[PDB]
Amino acid sequence: SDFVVIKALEDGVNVIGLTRGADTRFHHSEKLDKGEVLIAQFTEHTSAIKVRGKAYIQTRHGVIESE
Amino acid sequence: SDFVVIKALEDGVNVIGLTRGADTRFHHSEKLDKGEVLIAQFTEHTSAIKVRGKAYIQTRHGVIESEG
Amino acid sequence: NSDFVVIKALEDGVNVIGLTRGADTRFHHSEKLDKGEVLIAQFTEHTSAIKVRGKAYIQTRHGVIESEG
Amino acid sequence: SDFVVIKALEDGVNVIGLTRGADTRFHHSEKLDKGEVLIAQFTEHTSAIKVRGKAYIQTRHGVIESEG
Amino acid sequence: NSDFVVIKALEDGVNVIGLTRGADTRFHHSEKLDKGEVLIAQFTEHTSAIKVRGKAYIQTRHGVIESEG
Amino acid sequence: SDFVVIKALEDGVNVIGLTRGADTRFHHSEKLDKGEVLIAQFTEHTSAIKVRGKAYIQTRHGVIESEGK
Amino acid sequence: SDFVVIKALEDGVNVIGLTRGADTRFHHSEKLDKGEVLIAQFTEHTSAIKVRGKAYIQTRHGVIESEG
Amino acid sequence: SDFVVIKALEDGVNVIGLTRGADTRFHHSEKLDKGEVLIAQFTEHTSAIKVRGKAYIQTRHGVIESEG
Amino acid sequence: SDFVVIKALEDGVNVIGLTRGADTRFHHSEKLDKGEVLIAQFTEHTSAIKVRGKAYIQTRHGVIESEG
Amino acid sequence: SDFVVIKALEDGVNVIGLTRGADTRFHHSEKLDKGEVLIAQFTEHTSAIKVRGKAYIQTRHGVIESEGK
Amino acid sequence: SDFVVIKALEDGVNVIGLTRGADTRFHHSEKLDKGEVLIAQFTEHTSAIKVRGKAYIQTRHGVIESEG
Ligand SMILES: N[C@@H](Cc1c[nH]c2ccccc12)C(=O)O
Ligand SMILES: N[C@@H](Cc1c[nH]c2ccccc12)C(=O)O
Ligand SMILES: N[C@@H](Cc1c[nH]c2ccccc12)C(=O)O
Ligand SMILES: N[C@@H](Cc1c[nH]c2ccccc12)C(=O)O
Ligand SMILES: N[C@@H](Cc1c[nH]c2ccccc12)C(=O)O
Ligand SMILES: N[C@@H](Cc1c[nH]c2ccccc12)C(=O)O
Ligand SMILES: N[C@@H](Cc1c[nH]c2ccccc12)C(=O)O
Ligand SMILES: N[C@@H](Cc1c[nH]c2ccccc12)C(=O)O
Ligand SMILES: N[C@@H](Cc1c[nH]c2ccccc12)C(=O)O
Ligand SMILES: N[C@@H](Cc1c[nH]c2ccccc12)C(=O)O
Ligand SMILES: N[C@@H](Cc1c[nH]c2ccccc12)C(=O)O
């Protein structure tokens, strides 16, 4: 199953997981401080991922940056 | 399953999931504020995704941009 | 796990039309896009062909093609 | 499962689906007007596709053009 | 999910002949193409070999080849 | 499943299927005259293919030529 | 299943496994000292990994560096 | 499933199929005259193939040439 | 499964397997002397591998070096 | 399943298949003379292959050459 | 399933299988003299392979050389 790499470029970045299934809501928000990296898969419980805050992101489709 | 990356280039962008199945309707709209990124899969419940508003989108077939 | 098509409307009133899978072929849904909206649409248990009408920039795994209104 | 892209270069381009199975005949003809695009899969019901008329065609093996 | 061949007729009366899969081998269908028409034909449960007669431009996963009439 | 493309470069080329299994024998010989093309799979019944006669051959390993008699 | 390579560039780097499932929490934190390498899979129990401290990281998507 | 192409560079090239299983011996020998081509798979009954005589051979790992 | 190559660049390099499962602990420590090479899979019992000591390592993701 | 290509570069080359399982021993030694090519798979019964004698070898990882005593 | 190629560069090189399973111990040591080549899979019984002595090694990750 595929994954996303997120590197926080500032304190307070949120990596938020969205529920798989008929309904869509946030079930977890992981806080990243500056320089921390999270590598996060899609899973049985998480079919969409939202990033809030400034971070460097890598996926299979290349690099993108949130602000 | 494939996924799409959507980065909102202005406030109020909507990423809209359309129902899988014989019926087609919107089941969810995720609102993105400028500079937020959403990475969203195709799923048992979502077989088409629509984006409204200004955004930079990546998929397996390359970059495309939506404009508001 | 199926393939998908990206459609970006280059004018108002673009229609992305889904054709039914199976022995019966007909249109079952027509999605209206206005200028600059994007639809990323899979082939599905219900949709085995997709017709685009109106001016649009389309990406498939075979590359770019453009429809003209 | 594979698909063919068909872009009509004139009115009345006919995309013809041939039946899968021991018998071969057409079971559907989808006409396209100039500039419309049809992205059609091979399926449980369609194992061969014929294009009549002027059309620009993409498949996994590259581009080909039909002449009407 | 089988492979498919692309056949473009370069003259009228090209024949794309499907041969039967299985222990026995015979022609089960000849699809006749006129000049400029394109047939995209899979290998299937019933067709394990395809013969082209007449002048045609052909694409398969191993490249381009041309039949001559 | 893999296939081979055979284009006859003279009359009377044979494309010969050998039986799959513990027994090996020819079960079919498809005659090609000049300019005809056969695109033939490996199958539940054919696990080896012999070409006799002058032909241009494509497989997934590239181009090979058989030389006639 | 995919894996991530982490080389500690300073002492006390923490590679933290997050639980797979409805619940998300840290179930393990592996401490690396300077110059140690950990190569770590996604698994039945671990569906996200977090690195804290200065490290050089390789994944399928290329190289990235965490900072302390 | 993999296959090899064998082109005979002289008369009487011998393509030898070795039996798959705990035992090894040849179960079939197909002779090729000069210029003939055999395209042969690995199968339930053949798990090694030997070529005797001058032949031009292609496999997934490139070209090799047997000499008589 | 994926495997890692580890070449000891000094004596007493440790290639340590961490248990797969809810619990994470060392189950095995393989000591390599200078110049020895260990080629080691991920497996039913081993879902993370830690290298301590100076070594040259290859993974699908490319080269990395652990240092003493 | 993977296979290795072995071309003998002198008489008397041996390609030795080692048994798959908890037990490791030689179950078969195929003797090759100069110029002959063996294309051998890994199988239910053979999980390692040893080559003794001068030979030119291809595998998915590239060319390697065995040298005889 | 993958394999590794080992060419011995001097006499008495040892290619050592380590047991798959909860337990890790040797199980078999194949001695290669100079110039001999062994091509060995990962298997139900072997999940790690050690090379001791001077040898040229190829894996899917490239060339590496052990030193005695
Ligand atoms: N609960 C939704 C979440 C989702 C995934 N991808 C989306 C795309 C758009 C909107 C919502 C989603 C689902 O599993 O289908
Ligand atoms: N409910 C439709 C939604 C859909 C997916 N792709 C489409 C293409 C065109 C029109 C509708 C769609 C389906 O699951 O098949
Ligand atoms: N209902 C038809 C639709 C179709 C798909 N590809 C086509 C090509 C030509 C004509 C019809 C089709 C099918 O599922 O087979
Ligand atoms: N009914 C035929 C259609 C077909 C597919 N490919 C062909 C090639 C030649 C002739 C007919 C065909 C089949 O399913 O096999
Ligand atoms: N009925 C034969 C047709 C065939 C396929 N490929 C061939 C190659 C040679 C001769 C015959 C064939 C089969 O299914 O096997
Ligand atoms: N009956 C043999 C035919 C064959 C395939 N590949 C071969 C290679 C050599 C000799 C015979 C063969 C089989 O299916 O195994
Ligand atoms: N017992 C843990 C080991 C592990 C794998 N990857 C990790 C990443 C971080 C922390 C622990 C791990 C598991 O199988 O999941
Ligand atoms: N327990 C969560 C952990 C997780 C994986 N990826 C995520 C992305 C965002 C938030 C949480 C996660 C899950 O398995 O789904
Ligand atoms: N009967 C043997 C034939 C064989 C395949 N590859 C080999 C390598 C070496 C020696 C014999 C073999 C087997 O199926 O395993
Ligand atoms: N019987 C052993 C053969 C073997 C394969 N790979 C090896 C590597 C080293 C030593 C022995 C082996 C096994 O199947 O596992
Ligand atoms: N018996 C161990 C062998 C092993 C494979 N990879 C390793 C890495 C480190 C330590 C031991 C191992 C296992 O099957 O898991």
Image (cartoon, coloured by chain):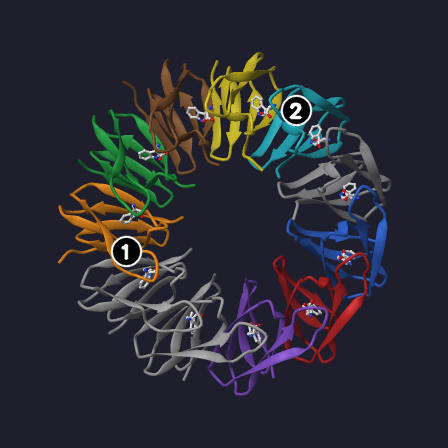
Chain colours: A red, B blue, D cyan, E yellow, F brown, G purple, H green, J orange
Q: Indicate the chain on which mark 2 is placed.
A: D
Q: Indicate the chain on which mark 1 is placed.
A: J
The residue positioned 55% from the left and 15% from the top of the image is: E14
Q: In the rendered structure, find residue F5 and report the number of the disc placed on it.
A: none
The residue positioned 30% from the left and 40% from the top of the image is: H19
Mark 1: give few (<14), some (14-19) or many (20+) Cα within 10 Å.
Answer: many
Asked whether residue A53 is in view, the answer is: no
User: Which amino acid lies under the numbered mark 1 shown in the image of this protein?
Assistant: Leu
Pointer 2 residue: D19
Above or below: residue B64 compared with residue E35 = below
Q: In the rendered structure, find residue J18 and report the number of the disc placed on it.
A: 1
User: Which amino acid lies under the numbered mark 2 shown in the image of this protein?
Assistant: Thr
Looking at this view, is A44 or D64 the one in front? A44
Callouts 1 and 2 close, C-beta under 8 Å? no
Residue G16: x %, y % from top left: 60, 78
Spatial CA distance of label 1 from label 2 is: 51 Å
Which tag is nearer the camera, tag 1 or tag 2?
Answer: 1
Find out if the beta carbon at label 1 lies less than 8 Å from the nearest ligand 10 atom.
yes
Asked whether residue E33 is in view, the answer is: yes
Q: Secondary structure at mark 1?
A: strand
Quadrant for ligand 1? bottom right
Residue G18: x %, y % from top left: 64, 74
Drawn side of residue F45 relative to residue H48, left or right: right
Drawn side of residue F13 relative to residue G12, left or right: left
Find out if the beta carbon at label 2 lies less than 8 Å from the nearest ligand 4 atom.
yes
Q: Secondary structure at mark 2?
A: strand
Residue A64: x %, y % from top left: 67, 63
Above or below: residue D44 compared with residue J46 = above
